[PDB]
Image (tube, rainbow, N blue to C red; front, side, top):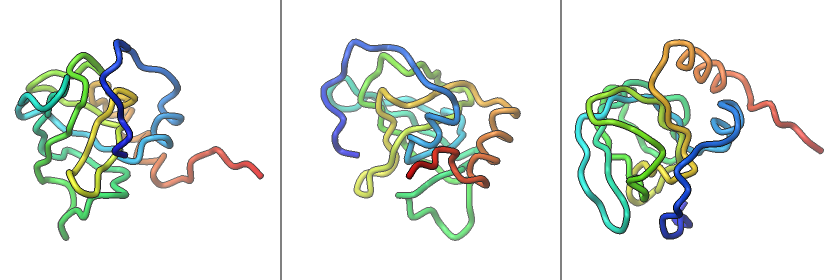
Length: 131
C-alpha cells in the first residue's frame, strides 16, 4: 500500500490480534537473519520465512514457506523487533517491491499459541460480517 507517509513519532501498537490480522494484507512468521538501513527513517529486516498465513500480493514459489525476504520497515523506531530473533509480522504487500511492514504493523515474538491461532484465523473467515 504505497500510501504510508513520513514516519510519525508514534512508537506503539493497538487493537486485538484478530482485528489486526484481518486488517493486515500480509501475515507471516519469520526469524530475522539481518538488518540493513533503507531510505528515509526506514530499515529493512532480512528474514527466512518460518511460516505464512496470508500472502495476497506475493507470487510465492511452487514449494511454500522456506524462502528469504526483506521486510521494508519505513520506521526504525517501532514496532519493536531484533536481529537474530523470531517474530510474527502482520503488515502489507507491495506488488512491485515485495513485503512491506508499515508502523501500523502488529509485531510480537513468535509463539506456538499465536501460530495455531493465526493458522485458524486463515482457515476461518475473518469475523466481521455487516450488511
